Length: 89
Length: 52
Image 1 (cartoon, rainbow over the protein chains, first blue to last red):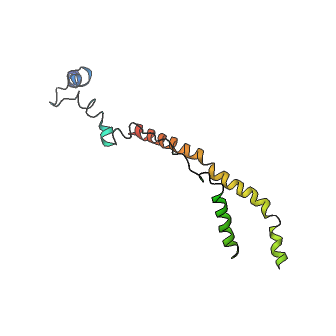
Image 2 (tube, chains in turn red, yellow; image 1 turned 90 degrees about the vertical axis):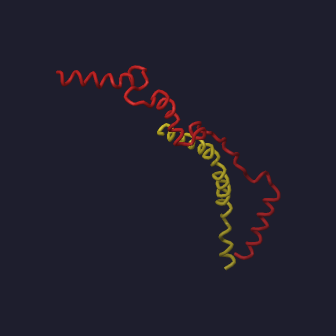
Image 3 (tube, rainbow over the protein chains, first blue to last red; image 1 turned 45 degrees about the vertical axis):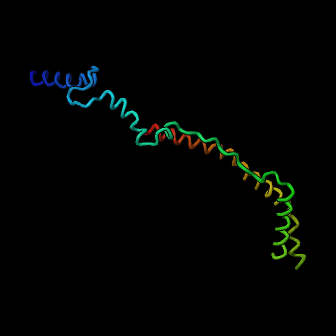
């Protein structure tokens, strides 16, 4: 079918240099080889936080603090404070 | 009335034993939760970044 074959190879050759062959891109002047593979490759990184989220910075968990080894002052102070409130129950 | 009031210290120590034990026990057993929090955050970041 002449209505078929010629439109078929026209729709094949126009993106042939675009996609199949490495002839940059003929239909539109701006280059595509250094744009989507190269300039837009950082596109997700450009929209997002580059070198901050794509690297997935892992912060080591800070050591959970405690009474800081206070076996005398803390216990005595707690006992005294409870004694203060025990007279007013 | 004082007798009735003192009747209630009879067994408070036995229960408050396990109470004071498990209080600090459970409060300090969240260390593994803290260690899991950073792993969960890393996993969330990974899923979000590959979704991106």
